[PDB]
Image 1 (cartoon, rainbow over the protein chains, first blue to last red):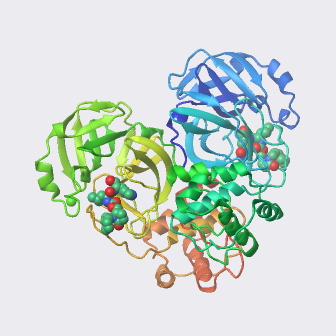
Image 2 (image 1 turned 90 degrees about the horizontal axis):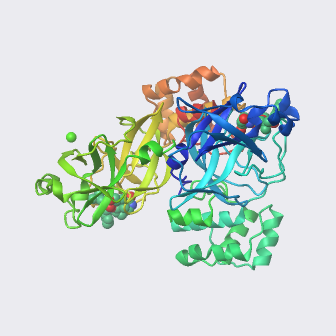
Image 3 (image 1 turned 180 degrees about the horizontal axis):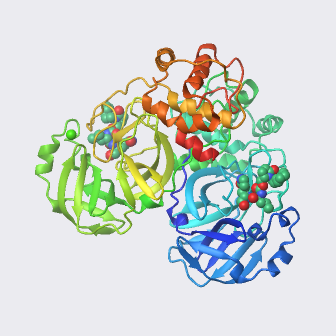
Length: 298
Length: 301
Ligand SMILES: *[C@@H](O)[C@H](C[C@@H]1CCNC1=O)NC(=O)[C@H](CC(C)C)NC(=O)OC[C@@H]1CCC(=O)N1CCC1CCCCC1
Ligand SMILES: *[C@@H](O)[C@H](C[C@@H]1CCNC1=O)NC(=O)[C@H](CC(C)C)NC(=O)OC[C@@H]1CCC(=O)N1CCC1CCCCC1
Ligand SMILES: [Ca+2]
C-alpha cells in the first residue's frame, strides 16, 4: 500500500513560465489568465518587506515575460488577488480542463505537480498539515507549482507553492492567493505552529494494513471516543470527531473492525510503541492517507 | 527524512493509453505511432488460462476480433502479431500524442513510475522499485494489466514495464515492452513463487550518500574494502551483491561528496556487522533501499 498521486496530464497542459527581472517561476494558465505567486515582482532588496501594491503599480504589462514552451504569451492585463498575480494574456489555453478552485481542510490530501521553468518534473501526494504546512519536495524555482485533486474529469486546484521554512517544510496559498497558515510572502525565517498528527488518517492507514493482512497491532480492548481523544491529545494527535468515525464506516464494515476498536489499537501503539515491529513497511505511524485515499486503492 | 517517492508527470503516457478487448476481457494497451502494445493474455479465455497455447490461440484470431478503443472511439486493427508475451496490434491511425520514446529493459533496483489504469482510464501514478527477485510492489487490481512503467528524460519517455500478473504473496510481475518477463515468470494462471527477496545494496548506498549530502555523516570511517570482500559480507545479511554497473551509477554521488564508492561500502559493511546502536540516519533507524542514485540527485539538486 503506497501513496498514489492523481494522473497529472490535465495540469501539465496548464503550466507556463513567468519571468520578471531576474526572477523566474511557474504559472498556471487557465483560459486566458495566468496565475502565479506575486513575489515574482520582488527584487533581492524588496523581498524583506515588500509593499506589493506599490511594487505592482510600478509594473507594466510588458515587464512580464510569459512563455508556454517556445511561445511567448503577450500580457494584456495584470491584477493581484491576495498573494497571487493574475496575468491576462491574448491567447486562450485550449488544454484548459474542467476545473474549480477549492480551499482544502487540514488533514486532506492532494497531488503536487512540481515544476521548474514551466516544465513539470515530478508528481507526488501531500497532506495539508494541521499546522498548515506541507511536507513537500520543492527546490529553488518551484514556486507556482500547484496541488490538486481530480474528481471525474474536473480538476480541483487547492494549492500554489510560495516558500520553504527553516525546518524544510513548505507553505503556500490557495488559488485565491490566501495562505494556508500564519505565513507571509516576505523573505524571512518563519516558524509554524506545533504540528500534530492527523488521527483519522492514521486510523485509515491501520485499516489499510489490516486489509493487506497485517494485524499484529489489533487488540480485544476497547475505548470510548472521549477517552481515546484524551490520550490522542496527550500525544499531540488531532481530535477524532463523530464525523471522522462516520467517515471510517466503510473501512470498518469491510474489515469487521469497529472504529473504536481500531482506536484502542492505536492507543496501545501510542502508549507502547511498535516494539521494533513495522506496519506496512514503516517504523512510524503514517498520517497522510485519508479514508478516501485508502478506499480508492482498497 | 526529507525524501519521498516522486513519480514522473504522467501526461505523456496518459496520451498513449487505450483499452483492448477480446470478448468480455478488457485490459489496457499502449498506443505509439500506429501500433498498440498489450499483454497477449487478452486472447485467453478462463479455460485457456491454466496453460494457454498462445500460438494456436492467435492463429484463430483475426484483426476484426480485437476491439481497440481510445475512450469510446474505436481504433481499427489492420494487423496483429505476437512478440514474446506482448501482442502488437497494428492500427490505421498514428497516435498524434505519441511522445519521443524508447523501450528499455531496466535492472533490479531501478525505479520507475507506474500509471495504473483500468479500462484505458488512468487512476493514479506512483513510483515502484524493481526488486532483486524481479517483482514489484504495485497497487494493481483486476483490470490493471497493460498498465505501464516508465521514466522520463528530457521529454523522452523510456517505457520499461507492462503489467501482467500478481503472485501469491501479493507482489506483481510483468514484462518489458518487447514482451520479455522480468524474472522467471510465465503468463499462465498458475502459482509462481518469487525468489527470496534481498535488500537493494546500491540504493542503500545512494541513501547513505544522501545522508552525507545533508550533513548526516557519523557512519563514515577511515577504511575501505574490495568489492569482492564487501559482496561476501553483503550476502550474509541478505543484501544484493554489487555489480560493476552499480559502482558506475554511484559515480556522480561519489564525486559530489568525494567519498569513494568502496569507502562507502566499508561504512555500510560496518553498519551491517555492528548495527546502528540506537542511532538514526536521515531520521530513521531503517536503511531505505527504494531510492536510486538518480532519485537522490533529483531530490537533492
Ligand atoms: C520560489 O520562488 C521559492 C521556493 C523555495 C526556494 C527553496 N525551496 C522553496 O520551496 N520561494 C522563495 O524564494 C521564497 C520567497 C519569499 C516568500 C519572498 N522564500 C523562501 O522560500 O525562502 C526559503 C529560505 C530557506 C529557509 C528559510 O528560512 N528561508 C526563508 C528566507 C531566508 C531566511 C534566513 C535569511 C535568508 C533568507
Ligand atoms: C490483469 O489481467 C491481471 C492483473 C491481476 C489481477 C489481480 N491483481 C493483478 O495484478 N492479471 C491476471 O489476471 C493474470 C492472468 C494470467 C497471467 C493469464 N493472473 C493473475 O494475476 O493471477 C493472480 C492470482 C491470484 C494470486 C495468484 O497467485 N494468482 C496466480 C494464478 C492462480 C490463482 C489461483 C490459485 C493459484 C494461482
Ligand atoms: Ca523470445
